[PDB]
Image (cartoon, rainbow, N blue to C red; front, top):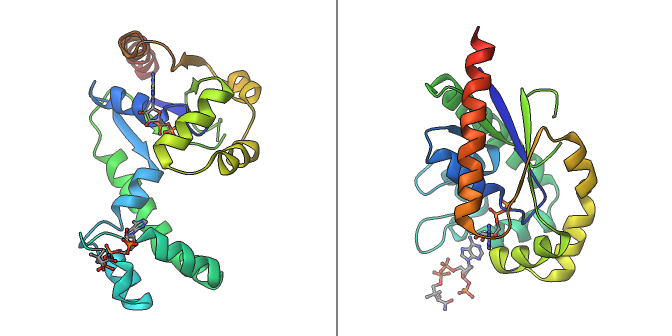
Length: 197
Ligand SMILES: Nc1ncnc2c1ncn2[C@@H]1O[C@H](COP(=O)(O)OP(=O)(O)O)[C@@H](O)[C@H]1O
């Protein structure tokens, strides 16, 4: 099934762009969003996390208290391995369930890392480094110090652009951005049909 890899540095707007493709009928696969769904209120994985570390891991609205989980993980690196063993298999299953359950002409695979050989096409969401730094501050509420260092750990802008088949500058007017997404959608639709034959 035709697959487009969506990638881009932190704060470039991957989620907003993927959400626009989603409103066009495209199946989006994002393990970051699936990981938060397998521990949503009432799920077995959240119960297990609470059974293990205590009810304080569940906040007033029945959702995971990620502050206390971070602290626990930070104080006991052994719990990260158990958390992985718990969640990783649930993310794999829910990833395949969404693939197998897709009737869309093509599939959008959100992948922050770059896994460039697994997809039929690579779409890079790009913005200037400064824009990356600010949009991180207001989206996550973190500090810039932490933002610069998160950005240092990732691939460089030139690296992403060099591996891209298509690029979308998530800057300027949203309408223009959404229009560019629609044009790419039409392109990918055609590449999917071509591939089918
Ligand atoms: N064209 C734009 N102008 C202003 N803010 C934007 C634009 N596009 C995206 N954003 C904002 O940037 C923030 C981070 O984007 P996000 O989708 O989280 O990127 P990523 O998923 O790559 O981290 C979001 O809060 C979003 O509202």
